[PDB]
């Protein structure tokens, strides 16, 4: 057993649509399922594989924006700030 926290139903949907290893994880575990989700869903640019385009996806509707970069993680962590509680203080 993991001994960690469950994100809300829409966010858990992204992670399960990716194939997550439970319903209880840390920020660093939950966000790893986004990387595998995009790699399976191939939501990145043809020109820039590290640039992500979630427009029309559940992950995009949940982000509230069609795009972010592997070099700019900020809006993911902000979508977690209010969806997911962590050990961090
Ligand atoms: C899925 C595409 C976009 O990912 C990549 C492609 C490239 C290129 N060119 C370079 C890097 C990745 C990358 N970098 C990480 C990452 C770590 C920390 C922060 C962030 Cl934001 C990203 C993580 C990932 C995790 C969450 C998300 Cl939301 C998206 C992507 N991520 C991967 O999931 N990877 C890299 C390793 N092998 C794989 O098969 C997939």
Image (tube, rainbow, N blue to C red):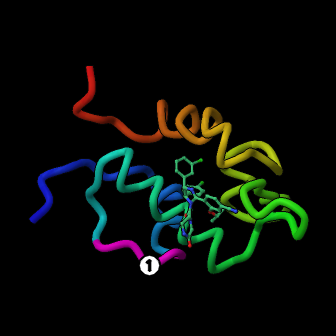
The secondary structure making up most of the magenta span is loop
Name the quadrant of the N terminus: bottom left
Q: Nearer the viewer, residue 11 or 89?
A: 89
Of residues 67 and 9, the one nearer the viewer is 67
Specify the farthest residue to the top.
89
Query: Is residue 87 positioned above or below 31 on the image?
Result: above
Q: Is residue 57 left or right of residue 34?
A: right
In which quadrant of the rendered image does the C terminus lie? top left
Tell me where the magenta segment starts and ends, as one range: 17-21
**Count of labels shown?**
1
Query: Where does label 1 land, which residue?
Result: 19
Residue 41 percent location from the top left of the image: 69, 77
Q: Secondary structure at mark 1?
A: loop
Which one is in front, 25 or 70?
70
Q: Can you give x and y, in whole percent of width and height, for residue 28 in the image? A: 37, 48
Residue at left offset 83%, top offset 50%: 66
């Amino acid at each position: 057993q993991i001994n960690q926290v469950r994100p809300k139903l829409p966010l858990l949907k992204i992670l399960h649509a990716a194939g997550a290893q439970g319903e209880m994880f840390t920020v660093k575990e939950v966000m790893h399922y986004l990387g595998q989700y995009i790699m399976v869903k191939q939501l990145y640019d043809q020109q820039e594989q590290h640039m992500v385009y979630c427009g029309g996806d559940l992950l995009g509707e949940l982000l509230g924006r069609q795009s972010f970069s592997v070099k700019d993680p900020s809006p993911l962590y902000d979508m977690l700030r209010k969806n997911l509680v962590t050990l961090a203080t």
